Image: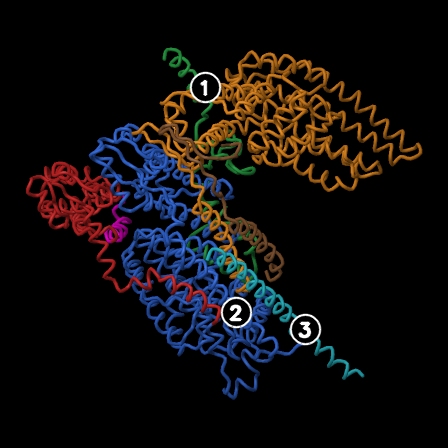
Amino acid sequence: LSESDKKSKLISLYLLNLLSQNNTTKFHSELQYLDKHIKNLEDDSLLSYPIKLDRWLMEGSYQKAWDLLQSGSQNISEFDSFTDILKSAIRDEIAKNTELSYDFLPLSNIKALLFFNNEKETEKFALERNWPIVNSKVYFNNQSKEKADYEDEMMHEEDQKTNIIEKAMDYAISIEN
Amino acid sequence: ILDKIFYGVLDQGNGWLYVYETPNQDATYDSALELVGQLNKVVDQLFEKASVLY
Amino acid sequence: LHHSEKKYAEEDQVQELLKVLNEISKTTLTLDPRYIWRSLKDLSSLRNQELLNAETLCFTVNVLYPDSSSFKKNLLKFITSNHKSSVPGSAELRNSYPASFYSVNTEKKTIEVTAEINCFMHLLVQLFLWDSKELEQLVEFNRKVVIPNLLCYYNLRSLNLINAKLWFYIYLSHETLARSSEEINSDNQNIILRSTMMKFLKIASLKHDNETKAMLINLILRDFLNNGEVDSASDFISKLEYPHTDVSSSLEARYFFYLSKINAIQLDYSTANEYIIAAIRKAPHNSKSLGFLQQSNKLHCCIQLLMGDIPELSFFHQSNMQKSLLPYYHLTKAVKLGDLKKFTSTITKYKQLLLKDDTYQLCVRLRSNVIKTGIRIISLTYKKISLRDICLKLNLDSEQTVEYMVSRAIRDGVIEAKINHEDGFIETTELLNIYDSEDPQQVFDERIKFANQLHDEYLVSMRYPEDKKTQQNEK
Amino acid sequence: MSTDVAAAQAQSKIDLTKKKNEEINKKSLEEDDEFEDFPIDTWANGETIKSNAVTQTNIWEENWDDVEVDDDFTNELKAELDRYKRENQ
Amino acid sequence: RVPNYEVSEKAFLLTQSKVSIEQRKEAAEFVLAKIKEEEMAPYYKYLCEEYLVNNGQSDLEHDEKSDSLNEWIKFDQELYNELCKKNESKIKELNEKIQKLEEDDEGELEQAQAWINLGEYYAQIGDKDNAEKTLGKSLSKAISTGAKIDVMLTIARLGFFYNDQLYVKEKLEAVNSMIEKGGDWERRNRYKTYYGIHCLAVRNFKEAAKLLVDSLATFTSIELTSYESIATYASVTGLFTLERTDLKSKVIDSPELLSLISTTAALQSISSLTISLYASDYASYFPYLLETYANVLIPCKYLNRHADFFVREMRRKVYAQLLESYKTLSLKSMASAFGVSVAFLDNDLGKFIPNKQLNCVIDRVNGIVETNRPDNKNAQYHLLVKQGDGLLTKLQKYGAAVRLT
Amino acid sequence: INISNNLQKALTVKTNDELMVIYISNLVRSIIAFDDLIENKIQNKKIQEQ
C-alpha cells in the first residue's frame, strides 16, 4: 500500500468499511497487515477515526461511538456513505446486550438508552428485534423465550447436552475396548 | 456460634435467628481428599525413578 | 601443512559419514536416524572451521562425485580461494571407502554412491553458510544450487528425512537478508521461496514422510506472521495435516506457538491460552532454549490479561528471566488496580520493548480490559451499588455511560450482573451453587475423557521398542 | 516460575547431544535469547531489592502487600477521625 | 556471643522512622557505649553500609547527608586505635596457647579448645568471617560430640547477627543431621529457639508457631536470647496460625505466658490483642491493633517484613468470626462496633473481598452487609477438582517425556 | 460419579507406571545387544590362538 498520497485516506476507508459490516475478527486481520507499514511511517492522522471507533465499541462505550460519528460529519467528505450504516451498528449492539440486562423499559427510557431520535423509531426497532409492546413497555424477556424455543427445534441437542443414560454407557465401553 | 453447640446465623438487619444443625461435610468427599493428595506426591516419586532414561 | 591438516580433518568426517551411510542404504528405522543427524551437526560445525576451509572441498574430490565438486568450488571462491592439496594425488584414494568403493569397482562403473553422498554433501554447503554467519553470495547461491537437485530425486523415504534439515538454513538466511536491506527484489524473492515450500508439502505427503511435512509448515507460518496476514495462516492450519507421527517435540513446540498468536487475535483466548501452556511443556527447558522460553512466558501472560485473568505475581519474581519481564510485572499490576492512568503511562515507556516481541498488538486491546477488571472488583465488593457511586470511584463521565459499559460485559457473561435502570442500581446476579444443576456431569465427562487418553497412549507405544530387541541378537 | 510446577519441567527436560541441534534451531527463529539482549538496550533493568523485603528475586514466598500501600498509616488515620466524629455524635 | 542480639535490635530502631525519636535516641546511646566496650567496630561498618540511603550517611566513611538523623552512628578515629590494639592483645595470647599445647600431651583436644576460643573472640567483635574458619578447625579434630553441635550453633548465631537467611539455613542443616547422633536434649531445645527465628523470618508461620510455643515450656537461655523476645515472638506467630479453639489452649491458657505477666510493653500489647479477639469484643480491638504494630512488630527486625500481613490478616480474622456467626449485618452496626465509621468500613472491606477472603457482599443501596459464604457441596467440589487438575497435567508431562526417549 | 472420577485418575498413574518400567528394560536391552557385537571379536581371537 502504495506510493500515492491518496494512501492515508484510502487505507482509512478500508478499515471504516469493515466496521459498518460488524466484523471485529476481520478488522484485526486486516489491521495487522497494515499495522507494520503505517505505524510511525504514516502515524494516525485520519487513521485514528476507525481505530478509536473500534476502541469505543470494545469498551462498551456506545455513547462515545455515537458522538464520534456526529463529529466526523463536521469534516464530511465521503464519510457519509458509512455514517448511515454505522449509526445502525450502534443501536443494534445495545439491543443484543440489553436482553441480558433489563426486563422492561418505558418508551422514554428505551429511546434515551439506545439513542432513538424520533418516537416512531422507538416502536419500529421493536418489531424488528421482535420485542412486543404492551402498555407502552418493551419486554426483553420475550426475546429470551424466543431464543429458548429455537434451542428446542434442534436435532443436535440429544448428543450435545448428552442424556444421563448415554454418559454412563460412554464411560463403560472405553474399558471394554 | 463459635463455641459450636447449635451454630446458626443471626440476622441483625431482619431480626431473626435461624438454626442450622445439619452436616457441614459428606464422608466420601473427605476420604477423597487424602486420596488425590497422595497421588500428587506419587507421580513425582515415579519420575524420580524413571529419569534414568534421561 | 595443507595436506597434513586437511587429511586429519577429513579422517574425523569419514567416521561420521559411515554412521549415516549404513542406515540410508539398508532402509531407515525413521526414529533412530533422525536423532543421529541432530548429534552429527554439532561435531561437523566445529570441524569445518577448524583446519582450513578447503577441507570440505578436498573431501568432495576424494569421495565419489557425479559433478558435486563444482558446487563446492564456487563457494570456496567467495570465502577466499584455495585449491591446493585438494586435487587428485593429494585428495584421491578409492580403497577402504565403500563410500567411493574399491579401485576395481569404480572402473567397472557398476556401483552407485553418487546419490546419498550428494545429499549429505549439501549439508556441508548449508553448514558452511551458517558457520561463517556471512550472507551475500552464500544466501542466493546455496538456495539455487541445492533445491533443483531435491526435485531431481524421485523422493524416497530415506532421502526425504535427510533433506528436511537443508530447509532451515535457506529460510533463516533469506529472512535475515530481508531484514538487513530494503529493496523490492527481496519482496519478490520472498514470494518464490514460499511457493517452493508449498509445492514440496504436497509431494512429501504422497510419499508419507513426516520430517519434511512438519518442517515446511513451521517455516512458512512464521513468514505469514511477520507480514501480518492472519488470513493466509488461518487457511494454512485448516488444511489440517500436520504430523505427529515421526517428529520431535521441539517441532510440536514450534507449531503450537504460531497457533496461539492467530487464535489470540481472532478473539478466541480460551484455546490460545490452552496451546501456549502446551507449547512451553512440549518444549525442552534449557539455556539454549532461552528465546523460546522467554517469549512463550511473555506471550502467555498477555493472553491471561486479554481474558481478564491476572498472571501470578510469583510467576515473574521467581523466574530467573525477571529482568526482561520488567514491563509485564508493571501491566499485570496496572490492570489489577484498575487505573486507567497507570496503564497509559506504563505502555508509553515500554512501547518499543512490546513492539519487539509482537506483544504490542495485544496491548492496544488491553486498553479495553482495564475498565472490565475495574468493574469485576466492583461486582465482587458490592452486590447493590448505585450508579453514582461507581462513577465517583472510577471517574466515569455519566450514569448512562457506565450502564452501557456494564451491559457489554454482562453480554459476554464475565461480570454476570443485571442492571436496573429505573431503580438506579446494578445488582450482581452471580451466586453459583451449581452442584444442584446438572453441570458437574459435564465437568466429569472431560476428566474421564482425559484419563482415557493416556490409557490408550501408553499401551500402543510400550510393546513397540520390545519387539526389536527380541528380534535382534543378545548376549 | 513457569506454568504449573517449574521444578517438574526442569527435572523432565535436560541437555542431550540429540536435543542440542533442536534447542538452538528453535531459539534462532524466535531470534536471540532476549535475556542478554535486553540489558544492552535499556541500560540495565532495575529490579528492586531496596524497596521490598521479599525482593524481586523471591527469597521464599512473596507478600502481595507490596501492591498495596502501607495501610497502617491509613488505619491509624481512620481511628482518629472516628474519635472526633464519635465524640460529637 | 551474648551482646549480638542486643546490639541488633537496638541498631534496627534507628533505621525506622515510624518509631518516635525518643525511643531511637535512647537506643543509640546504650549501644554506642557497648560498641566501644566490646570493640564491635567491624559490625559497626556493616551497619552504615547495608541500608544504604536513609540513615548511615553521618559517618566518617560516607559523606554526610541530612538523610541520617543519627550522629550517634558516627565513628571515632580513637575507636580504630583501640580496635587494633585489643585485637593483637587477645589474638596473640591464643596463638601462644596453640604453640604451647602442640608439645604437651593430648594436643587433639587442647589445640581444638584454643580454636573454640578464637571463635569466641571473633563473635565478640562482630566479624563472622575469620570466626567461620577457626570453628571449622575445632569441629575437625577430637572433641566431645555435643560440643560439635554447640560450635555449629555459634556459627549460626553470627549468621542471625548479620541477618543472612541463606547462611543460617546451612548452618542449621548440619545441626539437624547431628541432632539425634548426640541425642542431646540440651542442643535440641537450643535448636527449636534458633530455628524459631529462622522460621519467623520465613513467611511460613506454621512451623514458627510449632517451634516457638513449645520452646516456652522448657526454654534455654545458656548462650541464647532472652525469654522476653521469645514469649512475644511466640504469641505473634501463634495468633496467626492457631484457630480459636487451639488459641485458647496454647496462648491464653498457657501457664508460662501467664506467669511472665505484663512486664514488657511488647508483651502487654500482643496479650491484649488475643484476649479481645477471643472474648468477642470489637470496640477495643481497633485501637489495640494499632498499638501492637507500633511497639512490637516494628522494633523487631524479623516482623518488620511481616508487618503489613499482620494488619491485613488480623482484620480478616476478626471479620471471619463475625461473618460466620451472622447472615446479615448493617454497615451501620458493623462499623460502630469495631469503632470506625461507615465511610472507613467501606474501604477496609474493598481490600479483602476482591481477593476472595471473606466471601461476602455489601449492599450499598439497602445499607446492609450481606453474607454469602458457600459451605455447601459446590464449594467442596471446587477444591477437589483443583487437586485432580494439577495431577492430570503432571501425568501428561511425565508420561509424554518417557514416551519419546 | 465423583468417586468414579478419583478412581479413574488413580489407575492412570498405574498404567503410566507400567510404561515407565518397560522403557527401563528396553534401555538396558539396547546396551546388551551392543555388547554382543564387541564380544564376538573376543570369541574369534581365541579360535585362532588355541
Q: Which residues are magenta?
A: A26-39
Q: Which residue is mark 2?
A: C459
Q: Which chain is blue?
A: C
Q: Is residue C445 visible?
A: yes
Q: In this rendering, is residue C451 above or below E382?
A: below
- Identified by mark 3, the residue type is Asp
- Between A76 and C91, which is closer to the camera in this rendering? A76
- Between A174 and E103, which is closer to the camera in this rendering? A174
Q: CA distance from mark 3 to mark 1?
A: 79 Å
Quarter of the image for the C terminus of chain E: give it: bottom right
Main SS category, magenta section: helix
Q: Chain of mark 2?
A: C
Q: Residues within 10 Å of mark 1 (few under 14, many from 20)?
A: some
Q: In this rendering, is residue C19 above or below C102?
A: above
Q: Which residue is mark 3?
A: F35
Numbered disc 3: secondary structure: helix
Chain E, which colour? orange
Q: Which residue is mark 1?
A: D76
Q: Of circles 2 and 3, which is in front?
A: 2
Q: CA distance from mark 2 to mark 1?
A: 66 Å
- Identified by mark 1, the residue type is Glu
Q: Which chain is cyan?
A: F
Q: Chain of mark 3?
A: F
